[PDB]
Every structure is written in structure tokens, then in C-alpha cells.
Image (tube, rainbow, N blue to C red; front, side, top):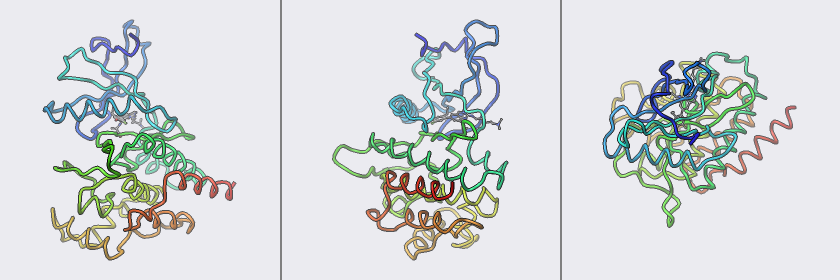
Length: 292
Ligand SMILES: CCc1cc(O)c(F)cc1-c1cc(N[C@@H](C)CO)c2nc(NCCCCCN(C)C)ncc2c1
């Protein structure tokens, strides 16, 4: 009943943007028409194909199954438009994406604060992994800011559930892929695992310590490394060979070496040699303790 959202009571307020296969709007759920309703984030599919509706229902099921302080809260589903025009209702996180929050404030968010966010992302990812879910899109653009003290993992649009018998999930026909955050085995074999999210987490830590400086983003740096003359599929071929030959993102300007050590550990070509999220959360917490 309260998790039952009727479309007629959903008042559009502003467009929030684009997700992993649809659009997000800020809506006020106002069943008393007095503008006193809760402000929510609503995902609706732009192109309701059979494969896309199926993926959206899986995302909705995945989000519903997650209860953690550092995972964006699922609120409900709005069916009023029929089962072919589903709306996902999430909590509204008013500070927006960590990418945009950090780009806005830059060095005003100190290393203590960045490691508090890093710790939270680890705890979110570790809980995610207990459920055998592979996020597949860990990036500061998909991490949301609740307040200056708490971040949460968002966009579960690419999340996969591991087979019962396997420690990886093979994507047979990939869609739009954030290749600059991808592990080598994800680029070569399209294999995703907890270990490939750890690789992506190392990229997020890189992102945090660059403070989203335009020319320092992972695509900018990797493109500079493989050559800005590389286009389309060729980018993927060269990126694979670069990673195989230990080409990596640089240490961000002013990054503590302790933190860069973690990034490079996440970026290990050997899948089995990557740290766990349990151990990353313990290590980042010990770093924060040594700083306080
Ligand atoms: C419903 C889509 C969705 C699906 C998922 O599976 C999921 F895990 C999360 C979300 C989702 C997606 C959002 N934004 C996208 C576009 C960016 O990643 C959210 N945006 C906000 N607040 C944004 C405020 C920005 C403005 C701030 N200025 C005023 C400074 N709150 C909650 C959000 C929740």
C-alpha cells in the first residue's frame, strides 16, 4: 500500500539526467495535492524493448534486495502505465553525483573526507558481493552524495548476478561499456566478477584523488597513452595491449603514496591477486585512523 505509487500522484519537478538505459526525473509524490509529498528520483525506460524491460525488471529486483547505508534506497515501483511502462522510485539524494560534488568543491574536500567516502564505497561494494552481485558500472558518476558525511552506490543498471556454479559472469553481446573503467579480462573476454569491480574501484579511487580535473579523467589519460589518433574498436585493441604491458593511470597530483599503492593493487592483471573489498575497507579505515 505505501510502496504503491500511482502515476497520477507523481508530479514532475526536474529532469535529473540519463541512467544506464533510461531517464531519471525528480518528482514529488503528492497524493494530497498540497505540494507536501516526498521528493523522489524516478527512473523510466526511454525505449521499452523486450530485452530492455527484462533488464530494468532485474535492476528493480536487485535494488529491492539491497539494504545498506551505502547503497541508494529503493522506494517502490509505479505500474499505473501498465507492466510495459514501469517506473522505479528511489530516494532522492540532494547533493547529486560524487563526480559533480567533487568537481564543484575540488581540494575543499580534504584527504580525510575522500577516505571516508572511499571507506563507504568499499562497505557498499562488500555487501553487494555477499549477494553475489557484480555492479559492472562502479564510477564516481554512479556514486551519489547524501550529505557531506555519506555517499551511496547508485546506477545498478548494468548489475549482474553470478551463476551459482561460477565466479564470473560472461556478457555475450555487450551494450554501451565504460571501457576505461574495465578490467583487462572484461575488455578481452567480457568476463565480470567481484575482482573486476575491485579493478573499477581502483579507478574510482584514482578519480577521487584527481578531484575530477578535466585533463586527468581516466579516458583522457588512457587516450593520451594509446594515442588520441585511435578511434572506435581500435581504442579497445590498444587499451588491452597497454594494460597487458603494465600501462596504468598515473599517481594523482598530491595523492598520498599509501593510497596510490591500493589503486595499483586493484589494477593487477592477475585476477586472483586483487584485494578483497573486506580487506580494502579494513586498510582504508586504518589509513583514516593514522590520519586523525
Ligand atoms: C532512478 C535511477 C537510479 C537507478 C538505480 O539503479 C540507482 F541505483 C540509482 C538511481 C538514481 C539516479 C540518480 N541520478 C543519475 C542521473 C546520476 O547517477 C539519482 N539522482 C539523485 N539526485 C540527483 C540530484 C542532482 C542535482 C544536484 N544539484 C542540485 C547540485 N538522487 C537519487 C538518484 C537515484
